[PDB]
Image 1 (tube, rainbow, N blue to C red):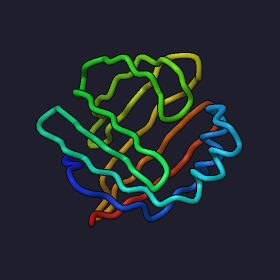
Image 2: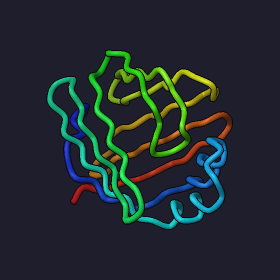
Image 3: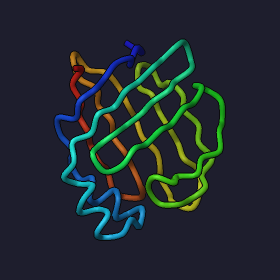
Image 4: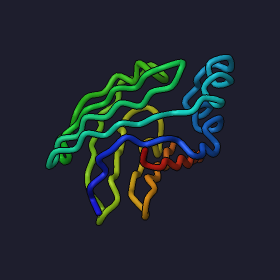
Length: 133
């Protein structure tokens, strides 16, 4: 399915530390970030996505239209400008963030009752698993 609608609760968060370090996020921020449960809300209407990922610490709001390039300023993470593009590869939602960092992006897909999100930066991969609430 390409339907990723819902309120999603984080089950696990593997190598978030490595991904953030690859993004040059400072030590103290990483130490807080790695321990927090995230909730991801996805409002998907055709090709229009509105997503909010939240924790006790920080919020990440990102909206996009599939197949439409958009500029991003990654204010909630490393503070960089990237050219982002989200597209479908089969049932996998694929984001490439073109800019300074190589192999920067993510892939997101539904398997059964779970949402999987794999974030990449350089040689680092963070794997997050969410279940629907």
